[PDB]
Image (tube, rainbow over all chains, first blue to last red):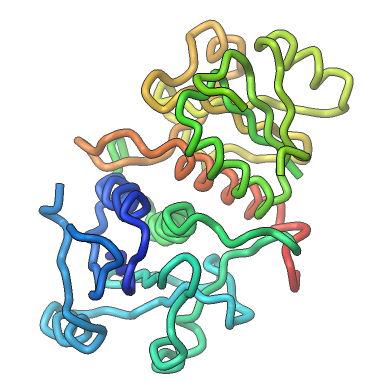
Length: 146
Length: 146
């Protein structure tokens, strides 16, 4: 239904959790280099840089990049997901650069609700939250017993 | 709006992630002993056993225990959450015992959708998924800018 992309991921254990998460919801995982670690992987694709990631997507049919950012008023539930959507996340401590975020329509910028004075989410929990909202809107197509 | 409870949690790093997660959605965290590790914590309460956990809840107004289990046809989106609900999770590798699950109405037993042949979810990702679905149904009451 959709894919997950990590921009320059930093913490290997998080990328480990996100690989398992991708198997549970049927997503393939895109890692945009450079990684903060050295690197089952049958659903994992590495891209040299953001532009190479875009060049790879153009050849593979319909897509939209939804960027996880605090720099928006729209939450992950307000977006309307479609087959081919890609859920993009920056490093846990830095988020995505402005040149990536500003390349996207305002409606493809999504923030996860949070209480005032809370710490950032663990990246893998943020992926799980957005991935399961996309999958909900797509009727959990592919789920066991469904 | 709601609280999270871990039955005999095993892996400390997961409990760490779930503490941060609880701060993001405004939940308090209940740990039902024994823990698999020795143990900010201002929102964390330890209970000697399941019955002590129930004795603590009875004195603190309206509640329902929703148990995360594969032993149900109903998914986390089919449940209708209310203020006072408690989201209960067993250890990642064992899940909850039958004597806990069977004490609950069938509508308080929830499973997260998953692809056939996927590994179990990391516990903290399963908590994030159910916690953010409850919070969605409760209008993300308390969220920044909301």
